[PDB]
Image (tube, rainbow, N blue to C red):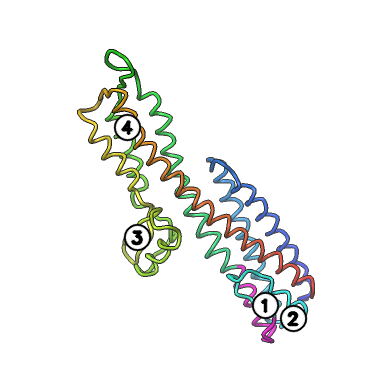
Amino acid sequence: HPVSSLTMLNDTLHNIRTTNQALKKELSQKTLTKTSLEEIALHSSQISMDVNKSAQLLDILSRHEYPINKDARELLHSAPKEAELDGDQMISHRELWAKIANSINDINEQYLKVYEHAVSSYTQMYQDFSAVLSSLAGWISPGGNDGNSVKLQVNSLKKALEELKEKYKDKPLYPANNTVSQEQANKWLTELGGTIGKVSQKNGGYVVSINMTPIDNMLKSLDNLGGNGEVVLDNAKYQAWNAGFSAEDETMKNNLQTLVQKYSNANSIFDNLVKVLSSTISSC
């Protein structure tokens, strides 16, 4: 009976915790590697399997209106504010078990998933830009005299750069696979910075897509360079350009970290949730 559900939910909750903790250590990392990413994808899907597994049990406890003592209820006060759980309020056990389940799904869907996408999306792109950098090394050679003059495969770099922007031109950061009101779309953008993404409309609604300004500025700088598809610039001119180029790179490098942050934070709140949720369950 619902008493087994009570114990199965604790197992599932402990599991969610195990996965979460494994995910955090991953995000505390320097380089969102192609591996560190699918690493997350698998960890998220797993967390999603348990949440649903939980939702199923939590639902049983609700229908059977399994009581939640005052003490166990008081424990809810320690859960995250975002969770939206009351340490009492003396409401139906049915509604409590329901709100709890809603909290697990809400956080996981509105926080974890929401950021696991923006983080993944941006990561993937910058990972494609880093591939260009690697190529940039074989695109520079000594030109002229030479005495520090540099030959740059303008076209080659321009071509690569215009393929990247293309690949991520319309890629969205939020929502992962849906639309929203331009008003609520402008909201999310203003909540994670504003420079990171750009509000746009596909159709059926609006979405916050990746801001390709850094790449545009990069192309504008290369266009200004001169004749194609090979240009030679003295040291002063090269460095000056590299400075600009390198700048743009860091702009993305930064935004990338910002996202990685909002994601880790979401992991924290979720973790705090399961931690007190588990204590609550136990106290039953």
Q: Residues within 10 Å of mark 2 (few under 14, many from 20)?
A: some
Task: Tell me the CA gap for discs 4 and 1.
Answer: 62 Å
- Is residue 175 in the magenta section? no
Task: Tell me the CA gap for discs 1 and 3.
Answer: 37 Å
Per the image, the residue denoted by label 2 is 66
Instruction: Give the residue type at disc 4.
Output: Ala
Give the x, y percent position of residue 248. 37, 41
Instruction: Give the residue type at disc 3.
Output: Val
Residues shaded magenta: 88-104
Secondary structure beneath dot 4 equals helix
Residue closest to the eye, 155 or 29:
29
Task: Tell me the CA gap for discs 4 and 2.
Answer: 70 Å
Per the image, the residue denoted by label 4 is 240
Per the image, the residue denoted by label 1 is 97
Task: Tell me the CA gap for discs 3 and 2.
Answer: 46 Å
Secondary structure beneath dot 3 equals strand
Q: Which of the marked residues, 1 or 2, is nearer the chain's N terminus?
A: 2
Residue 199 tag number: 3
Give the x, y percent position of residue 202. 32, 60
Q: Are marks 1 and 2 in contact (CB under 8 Å)?
A: yes
Secondary structure beneath dot 1 equals helix
Residue closest to the eye, 253 or 119:
253
Instruction: Give the residue type at disc 1.
Output: Trp
Which residue is located at x 38 percent, y 29 percent?
136
Q: Main secondary structure of the magenta part?
A: helix
The image quadrant of residue 50 is: bottom right
Q: Which callout, 4 or 2, points to the residue nearer the camera?
A: 4
Q: Residues within 10 Å of mark 4 (few under 14, many from 20)?
A: few
Give the x, y percent position of residue 198. 35, 56
Q: Which of the marked residues, 1 or 3, is nearer the chain's N terminus?
A: 1
The image quadrant of residue 274 is: bottom right
Secondary structure beneath dot 2 equals loop
